[PDB]
Image (cartoon, rainbow over all chains, first blue to last red; front, side, top):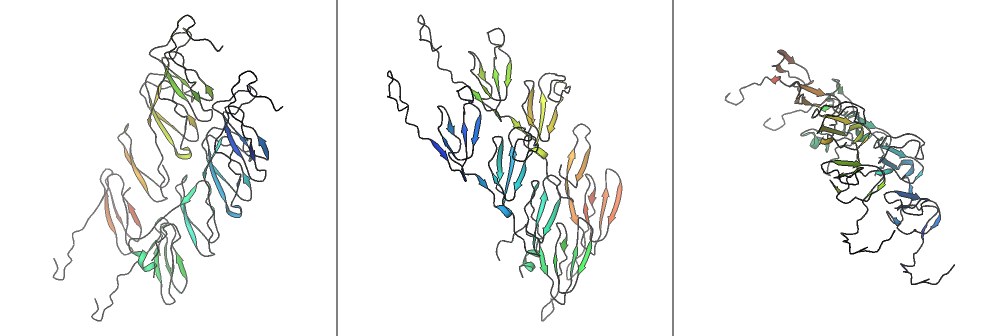
Length: 233
Length: 152
Length: 51
C-alpha cells in the first residue's frame, strides 16, 4: 500500500529507512531479532550476510551498524576466534568447538563471524628471509621454539616469545629498539669462532669460520673479557 | 491485557522493565524468588541462565544485576570455588561436595555458579618455558615442590 | 624457580637441605634450586694488593 497516517489517530513513530547490505562484501548483526512470534527475541541476535534489502522490524537494532565481510589477508591473513557458547559443526568448518576453546582460520577465504563466535585477533603472518626467524611460545605447552627460514603465521596456540643477554645486545648491533622476538643471529667474521652453549638442551657448540650463528630459545653467547691498550689493560 | 490504572483507586508502584538475559552469555540470581506460593521465598535465591525474558515478580530483586556466564580461560583458565551448604551429585559434574570442601574446574567449558556455590579464585595457569617453573605449596600437605618444564 | 647459568669454566656447589642431597654442578650447564637447596657462596680475595 501507501496508506494514510492516523488510520484512526495512530502514532506515526517514523518513516524507517531500509538497511541494505552490499552483496560482494557486507553483513551485520541485528539485536532482539524477531523469529516466528512476530515479536522480538529480546536477548538474541541474528546475522545476515548476502545482498539484501532489509527492513528493521520494530524493536530491532543493528549491533555494529553495517560491518563488511571479513575477506582474509589471504596468502597470509588470519582471524583467531573464541566462542561464547558451545556449538558443533555449526561454523563454516562443520567441526566441533567447545565453549571458549578458541582457534584460527586463515588462508584465501572470506569470513562472517558466526552468531556464537568472537573475533579475537586479526592475525597477520610474518614474512621471513631464508635465513631469519622468530621465537614462538606455545601458550598451551609452554614450548618456546625458534621458527626460522620461511614466512610464518602463529598457530592458534602460539604467540611470539622474547629474549636477550645482559650485555650481548651491544656487540650484536656491531641503534633502533632491538626486537626481542626476532631470532638472535650473529655473523661470525672470517677468522673467528664464537662459543655458544644451549642451556635447555645442554648442547655445547663452537661455530667457526665465516658462517653466521643463530641462538635457539635458550642458548647463550659466550662473552670475552679481553685486554687491549698500549699499556695493555 | 493493557489495563486501566486505579481499577478502584489502586496504587501503581511502577512500570517494571523486563530484565532480559542474553542467550550466549548472560545469567543471574534473583533474591526472594517466589515459588509455588505466589508469595516470596524470602531467605532464598533462584539462579537463571540462557536466553530469557524475565519479569521480576513483586518483591524479587536481582542479587548482582545481570551477570554474564563464565566461559573459562580455556586450555588454561580456571575457577576455584567453595560451597555454602553441603551438596551431592548437584554439580554439573554430578559430583558430591561437602560444605566448604572447595575445589576447581578448569578447561574448555562455560560455567554458572550454582545457588549453593561461590567463586573463590578466578585462577589463570602460568605459561612456563621448557626450562623454568614455579614453587607450589600444597596447603593440605604443606609439601613445597618445584614445578618446572611446562605451563602449569 | 631460582636458576643460574653456570659459566663454561666454572662449577657451583649446591646442597639440598630438606633432602640432604649434596651436588656440585660443573660445566657450562645451568642449575635451578629445589625448594630448600642453597647455593654455596664464596668470599674470595680480589684487590691489586690482595684484600
